[PDB]
Image 1: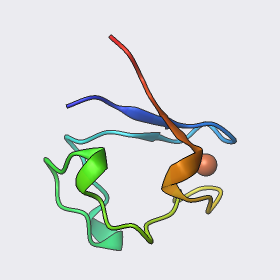
Image 2: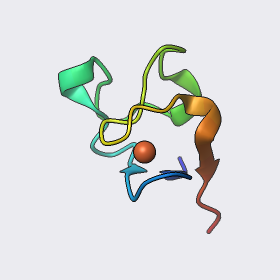
Image 3: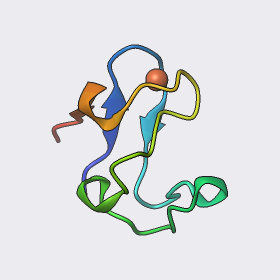
Amino acid sequence: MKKYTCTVCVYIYNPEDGDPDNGVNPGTDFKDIPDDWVCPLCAVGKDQFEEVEE
Ligand SMILES: [Fe+3]
């Protein structure tokens, strides 16, 4: 699983942490996050994220 970075703020989604306060368990792939999830810092949608290539 890849990290996905917000394109408009510094937030980085890390699958290992998930986003449990917003319902996303640890170990959740970015593609499986619910469609209405948003960036916890700037509130934009998943369509504004990019894969962090390795
Ligand atoms: Fe953001």
